[PDB]
Image (cartoon, rainbow, N blue to C red; front, side, top):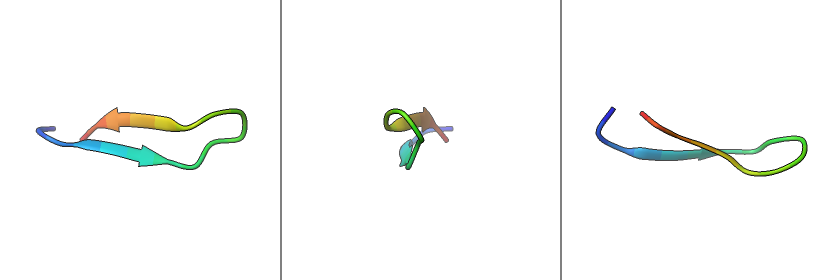
Length: 18
């Protein structure tokens, strides 16, 4: 939504807009 999140990936950092 109105926030930026970052989760651990297998190849690279996977961020999104929660």
